[PDB]
Image 1: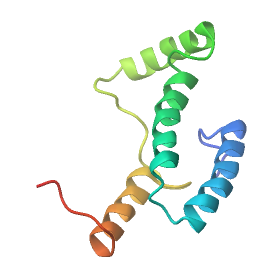
Image 2: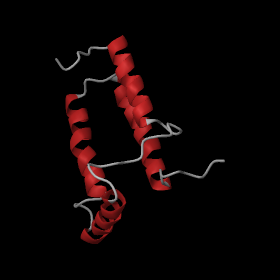
Image 3: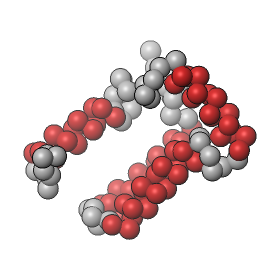
Image 4: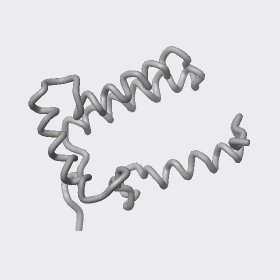
Length: 112
């Protein structure tokens, strides 16, 4: 049993695909280290998520997102957000794979 998209909407889908092309693109040839690029991802990162649903793009929509996640998340505390399926990409999964690879072969050092 599989549904179109658990959550990842179409639009997003397009953003992820194009984001992958560009991502892997620069991140590829360049590999990484992008100080400005990465920094751009951080800024636009939070602004993207928050802005997308917080306060930046349309006061109404955002508001709709405030009440939406307000109650949805309200049920719980701290944050409580999906993170158990690793069907698509895998947050905890992939992440774990990242950290693993990090400790494996990559400039990394535990938070001493």
